[PDB]
Every structure is written in C-alpha cells, then in structure tokens.
Length: 330
Image (cartoon, rainbow, N blue to C red; front, side, top):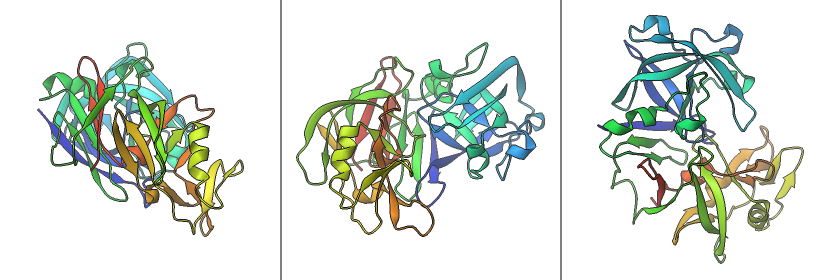
C-alpha cells in the first residue's frame, strides 16, 4: 500500500504545516502537524477542557463506531518550545492520503497549553519519530508509520515541504518526479529516538564550504534551523546590522536586508537554502526588525534541521531495518 497527502503552511511565514487526517468511522477529518521530532498522535477532542479550545476541529470518539477506549492508558508530552498536552487514549482507524491503519492509538487531549489553544489551525500532532519516544503509559504505543510499515510497498515516508506553498507527505514510495538529480543517503542514529544524522558541513552565501561534522535531527515539527553558535555567528556576520537580541530571543536583522543563502552538506552532496527561506518577517507588526530563520542551538542540547532546512530538499525517511535519511535537491 501507499498514501499521499498534501501538507499546507498554516500562515504566510510557514510557521508550521498541516495535513488532513481521517480518524474514525464515519471519518472525522482533522488537520494535524506531522512531526518527525516526536512520536505521539494526539488530537483536540470532545474531552479537551472547553476553555482551552479556540477554533480547532475536535475528534469525538463517541461518534466513531470503531473507537475503543484504551483502558487505563494516559499520555503527557512536552515540546522544545515549552508547549505541552496530556490526556487519555483511544484506538481507532486512521487514514492519511488513502493509507489506512486500524487500531492506531489516538491520544485524546484533556489539557493543552496556551500555545496550542492559540493556534486555531492545528488540530493536533502526528508523530513520525521512533516509537521509543511515545509517551503513552503504562503500555507504550506505536506511531502511524510504525503501524503502517509492514503493509507499505517500501518502508519509507517522504517529506516535500513547500516554501510559502503546499507540499506533500508520501508513505510507501519515492516519487522520482519530485526531486532533481540524485538522492544522497546518510546514516541515522536512533539512540535518542530521533532521525538523527551528521551533516558534513556548511557554506554561507557564495563562500567556501567548511567541512565539519554537525550532528542534528531532521524535525518537521520545528520551524527554524538551529545550529551551533559558531555556525550561526558566521552566517549572520554576512548580514549588515544583524545581531543577537536577548530581548527578542535570537538573531534579528534589518528588514531591508537581502539575506545570503545557507548550504548544508549531506555526505558529498549539498543542499542550498535560499536566503528568502531564512526571513521570518517583522518581530512584531510594523517593525523594521525581522526575525532570523537560522538560530543558535546553544542550550537546546541538540542541533535541529527544522522546516527552514527541510523545505529546501526532498527528504526520505527510510525506516528499513537499519534506518537512513535521504536528501535531494528539488
């Protein structure tokens, strides 16, 4: 089997991407944030504290003839941006782009933090990291991909995120029309539960490539590119007037700037992030200070190849017995 679903930016900055997901019988379609950095499929629901729901579409398990309470199971998760959610668990039928899993754990939120409430466009998350990170207790649950894998034509999914445009998540096949040149594959460590890999270096604009190993994670649920302070300083030094602002919470730059590209290495291959992808717009409405899309990972504890990086590539998440990651230009 295979599946193919369009993923759409939630706003004009590509702050996140939402993908429609069918849950239950009859189908209830929710728009979920596919997150290769976590491993829980959770939704706003009829159980979510009413004051914490503001415009989201909810899953109502009592209206699904295939929903079953997973008795005694609870979940609770916190994300790198400080947001969080928790609740109980149902199993139900879940379909993405025509690919159906029966008995998928659907984690129903009883509580969500303010950042979730405030984002009316995101109805929940669909985790695509390794199932070892799943938070359900006392019986850990599998991700949608893990459940689907054996049925797929090939044990893979691909992320093809758009810049200020829709893109695609495919399950079970590689669309050879969706990228240019060849796909370069690179080793993955699953030791921390992430799609963790090592970039071979970077370049800023038309500058020379610096060969240096940068361990980090491919994370579709993180907006920006978080890299070591040395790398980030080298980038922003090429933008007149750019500076790190403790009050704003990262590097800012004059909105009048033209940003240089940023290249990262995948083995001997190179992925080029155009400068425009690094512009996250005014820090506040009407400001002439703009927020940068490349930020320091110092104090995160891990480097994160978030959407800024991934949307410059066609990315293969190869879930074969020994997982690997593939990157192609597009």
